[PDB]
Image (cartoon, rainbow, N blue to C red):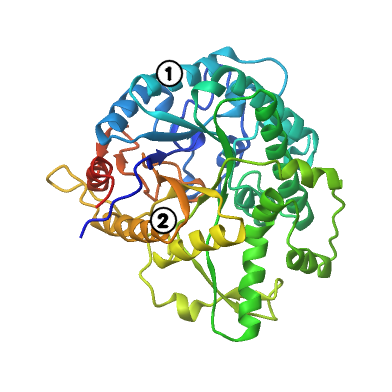
Amino acid sequence: SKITFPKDFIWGSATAAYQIEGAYNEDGKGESIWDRFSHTPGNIADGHTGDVACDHYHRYEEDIKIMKEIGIKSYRFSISWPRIFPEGTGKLNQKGLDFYKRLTNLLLENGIMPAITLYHWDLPQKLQDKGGWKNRDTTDYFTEYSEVIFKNLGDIVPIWFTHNEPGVVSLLGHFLGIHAPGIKDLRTSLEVSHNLLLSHGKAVKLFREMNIDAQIGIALNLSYHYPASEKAEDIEAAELSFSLAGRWYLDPVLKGRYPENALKLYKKKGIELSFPEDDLKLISQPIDFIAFNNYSSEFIKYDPSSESGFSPANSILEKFEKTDMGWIIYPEGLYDLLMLLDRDYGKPNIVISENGAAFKDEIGSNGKIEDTKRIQYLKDYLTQAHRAIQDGVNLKAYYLWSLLDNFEWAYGYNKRFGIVHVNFDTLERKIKDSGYWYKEVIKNNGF
């Protein structure tokens, strides 16, 4: 029987610029680090690139029509810094800015609330040539970019996110090197994590200084990390796991410190950090909500052989349903994560900035996409979200990742997360059943 969400609850859908826009070298847009990373064989599945993607730069009018028909209340998208400042600083590319001005106006005219992410991973390559996020100057350039954006859009865009998933940019982009810019250095990765947090602080401070009449936050990748067993060493391994992945970004932002057990670990590996203590005060500027991207959960065991003292519990993992990513399905995970946030960070306002899943989608001979595995996933995860609202969590919005099938970073176009199907040869859009379903969910404020 039917569940119903709070009355003001915001039903949304999300994208990112490099994943959908294409037009990678049009209207003076500067090269980003993802253009550079995508142009190198071996980096992306099948040699895919974001050169064209869903061509949303040209087709946004069609895409807005689709949103209005599904009935989403908020549309989360990101702005491409290299379209605004091709060289990352210097002179302003008005054609790029007009794109977003127009986009935002068309959303508001169709009754859709904009939610903007300022950085979703596309640093201008010119700034990467001078060290990128390892160079503290990038945090000032980011603020200059944010200023232009706040000046033109601030008051008419009710939801802002400084950054998407600084932890991924950090680990995958500067440690593992499987994301742009493909650097492999532990220490570099930690300087980067810090400069990303700094840049967030500076933009929040700027936002208040310009007295923008809207809510700002940050979107972190979060996942509940469960201990493999009740044994003490497993409890500690999971908490260490969560500290390195989640508390490393939550604690600076919401409590003005780094987690101690993670600093311990990195000390053991030869790395101590000297942060101006005034930086942590910048980083913990008050924000109006905390947001996170969640898909799955982790299971973690003590592991002395590992570089980090822990590793995944593959035994346990082998026993759940998996998505097309190889990720476990475990809806209770979202409840536990929501409760953790509520309990450990003083009952903050919470946005789910992303949630979704990827399954092999086929268009049937009937011309439709009957993606019932995705509908089941969404049903299941949303039931757990609802449960957590009941138990007193302040969850205000849910953004379904993704509106459109898109360039999924290192996996290219092989992994579909959309509620709208995209044929990447013809660029035609077909609303999937998950989309039709979501339409009804929104109508009814639940299911």
Q: Amino acid at mark 1?
A: Asn
Classed neighbour count for the residue bearing mark 1: other residues with Cα under 10 Å, few (<14), some (14–19), many (≥20): some
Asked if residue 153 shows in the view, the reply is yes
Q: Residue at x 67, y 50 (%)?
A: 254
Q: CA distance from mark 1 to mark 2?
A: 32 Å
Q: Is residue 213 left or right of residue 378?
A: right
| Residue closer to the observer: 17 or 385 | 385
Q: Secondary structure at mark 1?
A: helix
Q: Secondary structure at mark 2?
A: helix
Residue wearing tag 1: 105
Asked if residue 426 shows in the view, the reply is no
* Image position, residue 56 (x, y; %): 40, 28
Q: Residue at x 64, y 24 (%)?
A: 211
Q: Amino acid at mark 2?
A: Ile
User: If the image is split into quadrants, where does the N terminus sit?
Assistant: bottom left
| Residue closer to the observer: 289 or 424 | 289
Q: Residue at x 65, y 29 (%)?
A: 207
**Mark 1 vs 2, N-terminal side:** 1
* Image position, residue 145 (x, y; %): 66, 25
* Total marks in image: 2
**Residue 389 bears which disc, if any?**
2
Classed neighbour count for the residue bearing mark 2: other residues with Cα under 10 Å, few (<14), some (14–19), many (≥20): some
Circles 1, 2 touching at the beta carbon (< 8 Å): no
Residue 62 vertical position relative to residue 184 in the rendered view, above or below: above
